[PDB]
Amino acid sequence: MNFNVGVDFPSFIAWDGEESFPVKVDGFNQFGFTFKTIAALTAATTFNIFYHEPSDADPCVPGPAIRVPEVPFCDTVLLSEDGLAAVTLPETVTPDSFCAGTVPCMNGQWISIAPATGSETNAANVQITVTMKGATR
Amino acid sequence: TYMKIADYGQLGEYTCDAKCDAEFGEPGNIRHLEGKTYDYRGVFCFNRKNLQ
Image 1: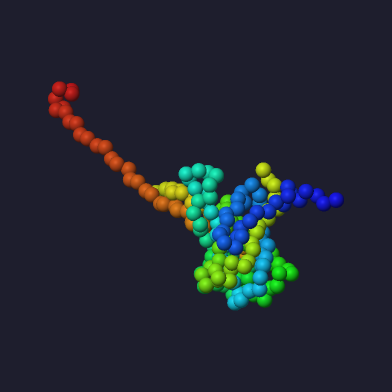
Image 2: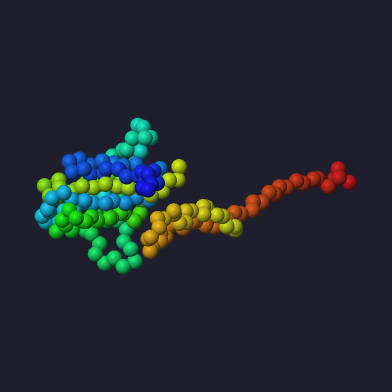
């Protein structure tokens, strides 16, 4: 009796392992990631977060790639060098469980993920995807 | 002398949620002007002989 859970929380591909992908997050209002690996890892990979603005050439094409400023919670004593919230996937993660991260404040209409420098060679074996929660059309 | 309100200025933005913080915005402005009063005078005389 599986409900068609496509509608009511659809999902899209952000990082397939070779090239990033912007996803539209305007129609919806609550989103998150589910990191996934295929093969064993090495030194913990890190990931940049990005947000886009609708390019003025067409209000339905994602513009350039801008990085999202980081916000801390009430008890966050470990701020990165700059802001620009990033996610470092802790290594030693076999393909038998996943992780579920999300930025705490949305700003833009297109979220994008990309591996930071010095991770690419170890980032080709990770598998990222995103899923919304709202409807609000 | 009288006061004037330059502009109320912006106070508070649409901040995100889950942000234990706030923003000071930008205070307004209140000038204090003043102005004088000018006088207007003149003179006119007679001869006192034809006035009688």
